[PDB]
């Protein structure tokens, strides 16, 4: 189990390496055997979509004391948590764990 | 809609009136036309079970700010909320509303 947390897989999802092909600018009229180091500058754009279906294990604890949950505090503040600032920068205030429910040993 | 809250029904669930029948103690040997006011003291016991199936309307709001929820405060205290005291008396500390989720007008 990777010590930073997560899932340990012998065959994780593969890398997706993307490269935009070189297109040489204008090679000489006379032959030359070198690597043709003069390429025209360019880049790319698009979209990338990652649909990754999870499987859940619902909880059925017979606990009577109300569970402890994760909530966002109701109190007036300059910015909503997990919402963009006046300039447009998306700010995440705190790390969110995944251990909130309680299950007896 | 009953002003104390709840559901207004033209035909609510009926009353269930329970009475343990009189059993006269020992009427006289001679006839007497009165109401026979001497009954033997008694009571009853049992169990009562009320299964009342509700119907829910699940929520599908596309809100991004985390919803506001009802939780029990994580802080050391002499008694667990909604749990019995040292003597055995079940104590409910606060009234619990039913309006916590948020739905836009």
Image: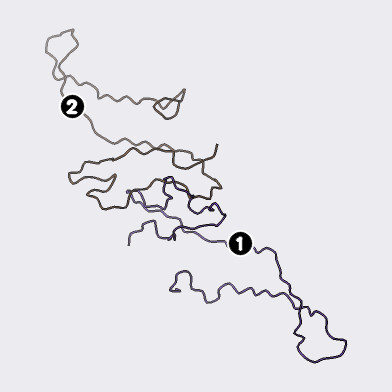
Chain colours: A brown, B purple
Of residues B13 and A23, which is closer to you in this image? B13
For label 2, count other residues whose C-alpha is less than 10 Å away and answer few (under 14), some (14-19) or many (20+).
few
For label 1, count other residues whose C-alpha is less than 10 Å away and answer few (under 14), some (14-19) or many (20+).
few
Chain letter behind tag 1: B
Of residues A41 and A76, which is closer to you in this image? A76
Of residues B34 and B99, which is closer to you in this image? B34
Estimate the x, y position of residue B63 in percent, counting from the top left: 34, 51
Estimate the x, y position of residue B26 in percent, counting from the top left: 83, 81
Task: Say which quadrant the C terminus of chain B sits in.
Answer: bottom left
Which residue does the image show at 48% across and 73% down from the upper left?
B8
Q: Is residue B31 above or below residue A7?
A: below
The residue identified by callout 1 is: B51
Q: Which residue is situated farthest in the bottom direction here?
A: B33
Which residue does the image show at 61% across and 74% down from the upper left?
B15
Q: In the image, is B27 to the left or to the right of B15?
A: right
The residue identified by callout 2 is: A42
């Amino acid at each position: 189990s990777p010590l930073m947390g997560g899932f340990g897989m012998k065959h994780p999802p593969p890398q997706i390496l993307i490269k935009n092909t070189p297109v040489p600018a204008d090679p000489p009229t006379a032959f030359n055997k070198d690597k043709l180091n003069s390429f025209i500058t360019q880049y790319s754009t698009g979209q990338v979509s990652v649909e990754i279906e999870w499987e859940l294990q619902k909880e059925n604890s017979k606990r009577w004391n109300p569970e402890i949950q994760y909530t966002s505090n109701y109190y007036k503040s300059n910015n909503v948590e997990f919402a963009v600032n006046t300039e447009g920068v998306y700010s995440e205030p705190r790390p969110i764990g995944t251990r909130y429910l309680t299950r007896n040993l």
